Amino acid sequence: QEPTWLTDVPAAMEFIAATEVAVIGFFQDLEIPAVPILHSMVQKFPGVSFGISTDSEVLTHYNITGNTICLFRLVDNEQLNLEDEDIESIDATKLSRFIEINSLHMVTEYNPVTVIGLFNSVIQIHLLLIMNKASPEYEENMHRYQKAAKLFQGKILFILVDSGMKENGKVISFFKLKESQLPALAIYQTLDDEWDTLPTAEVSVEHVQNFCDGFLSGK
């Protein structure tokens, strides 16, 4: 596949808004390795919209000064730049990992890569839904979790922790929760120590919303 050409500001915003995660190359000239490198990511990241613009007014709207590749994401309205020497010495693996790390969605799956992205968002409150992907109720619970995530966008990053995976045993045990108590919610702060849990949760929008609104209270 190939990146979509972006010729004006309304076309660019629309392109970025149509997708939870967009990656756009903003170039003052196409004679740099960033362009084919950017092209090569498309087939690799099927869940990302790739665009490209040389248009002056586009670059200006996004406050671009010189060759920059940006990742945009709905969930926290972020715009992350790969600029200057990052882009000068850009290779595919560095762009690849940058996209992996920072591809946060309305609900992001938890793994050691995404957690880096999650911890570096301006949003400092994280919610975990800890349950097993092989549960009967996984789909329904997840849909409802997605619905509640919309209610708190800009405020809380909704995350899924698949308890069906060994790697996640330690994160689950930090919150003093056991397998038999799942599905459960755990909410915490990136810069502060307080957290809370809702063991044996019913994952209804109302329950999730109440749990979040309680945590947000006062802070």
Image (cartoon, grey):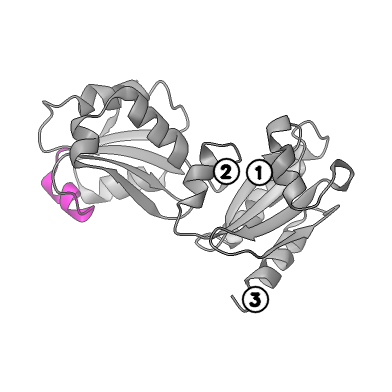
Q: In the displayed orientation, state which residue is furthest to the bottom.
A: 218
Q: Amino acid at mark 3?
A: Ser
Question: Would you name the residue on which mark 3 appears?
Answer: 217
Q: Are marks 2 and 1 in contact (CB under 8 Å)?
A: yes
**SS under mark 3:** loop
Q: Residues within 10 Å of mark 1 (few under 14, many from 20)?
A: many
Please tell me which residue lies in front, 69 or 170.
170
Find residue 192 and report its horizontal and vertical position in percent: 58, 64
Q: Going from the N terminus, do you reach mark 2 or mark 1 first? A: 2
Q: Amino acid at mark 1?
A: Leu
**SS under mark 1:** strand
> Is 57 in the magenta?
yes
**SS under mark 2:** strand
Q: CA distance from mark 2 to mark 1?
A: 6 Å
Residue at 75% x, 37% y is: 163
Q: Going from the N terminus, do you reach mark 2 or mark 3 first? A: 2
Can you say which quadrant of the picture contains the N terminus? top left
Question: Would you name the residue on which mark 1 appears?
Answer: 160
Please tell me which residue lies in front, 153 or 91.
91
Q: Is residue 117 left or right of residue 26?
A: right
Residue at 42% x, 44% y is: 18
Number of numbered labels in the structure image:
3
Q: CA distance from mark 2 to mark 3?
A: 24 Å
Find residue 159 and report its horizontal and vertical position in percent: 62, 47
Q: Is residue 71 visible?
A: yes
Q: Quadrant of residue 151?
A: bottom right
Question: Would you name the residue on which mark 2 appears?
Answer: 108
Q: Amino acid at mark 2?
A: Thr
Q: Is residue 48 visible?
A: no
Q: Residues within 10 Å of mark 3 (few under 14, many from 20)?
A: few
Find residue 196 and report its horizontal and vertical position in percent: 73, 62
Q: Which residues are magenta?
A: 53-64
